[PDB]
Image (cartoon, rainbow, N blue to C red):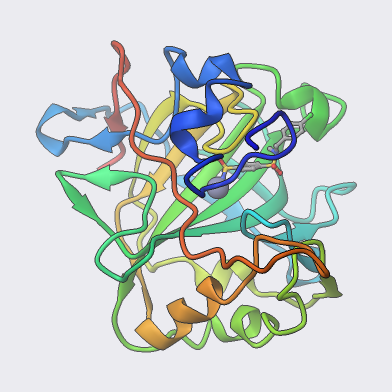
Length: 262
Ligand SMILES: CN(Cc1ccc(Cl)cc1)S(=O)(=O)c1ccc(S(N)(=O)=O)cc1
Ligand SMILES: [Zn+2]
């Protein structure tokens, strides 16, 4: 029961099957990717990242069945990403997390054969050119996603505000008010990054993303990370399954180059 609404990460509907309903899964700019550092193009024309996140932008946290979503008010330019490889201003919309079944893997991007325990995605859209997230999502330059690796280490109290909420939203489709979220404090100290043209890592897998993957990981404890696997991918009433893993394997580069800021 894989379909154009019923995709997932289980055996019958996981990544291997997404192509059945989203043929672009086999496209030439699919994400995520293994970054081979020896092959990175160190580009002196890449600018520093400019990041401004207003803690009051966050409105709600939700269980989609595929991850947790922190959703932000994107009607104003309070929370925006500029610089790096980007032209103009990209407005903050959504935060996701990806993880695997155990702490030794779970990230979407892989760096020199190494997988991190999880990966945070910060999703933004080009509001200087496009009227809306929906319109931007189907343009090559419409979206910018900031990726941050999570490694097992000392408990991160920055993750605590999110993990404290996870019982509220256990069932697929539950949401809770979630505000005064200091996203910028969750980022690592250094904003050195890789960048490449790609796609959404989930259906519908649109090739509209400028990926900006931060070199420096942040921490998560094993017991924090296990909270996310207690989320259900099934709705209230239906037969319970856990969201034990929600990452897409790396995809073919097909001529693309990864550029480094550093
Ligand atoms: C981008 N969304 C999917 C989507 C995009 C466009 C439209 Cl018109 C409808 C749905 S999303 O909120 O489900 C989303 C965004 C970004 C990513 S990711 N994990 O690649 O950065 C996943 C999912
Ligand atoms: Zn994501």
